[PDB]
Structure formats: structure tokens, C-alpha cells
Length: 26
Image (cartoon, rainbow, N blue to C red; front, side, top):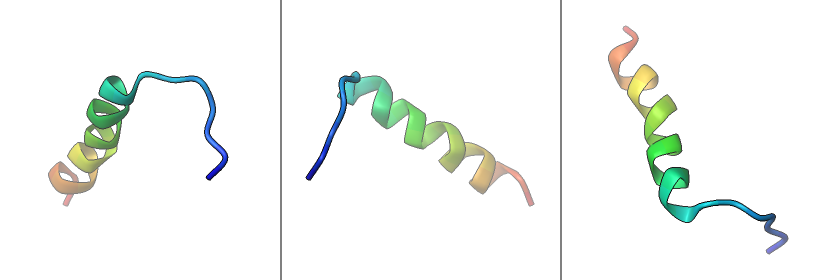
């Protein structure tokens, strides 16, 4: 898969970022 330069860690926290809103936002 074509990937770019980034932090796989934050990446998770990032997914978590929306996952957060997505979960928190009703």
C-alpha cells in the first residue's frame, strides 16, 4: 500500500481523535 511519512503512534491517537468525536458526538 502507498504510505507517506508519519508517526504510527500519533496516527493511532489521531484515529482516536476522530474516533473520539465520532464516539463522543451524539
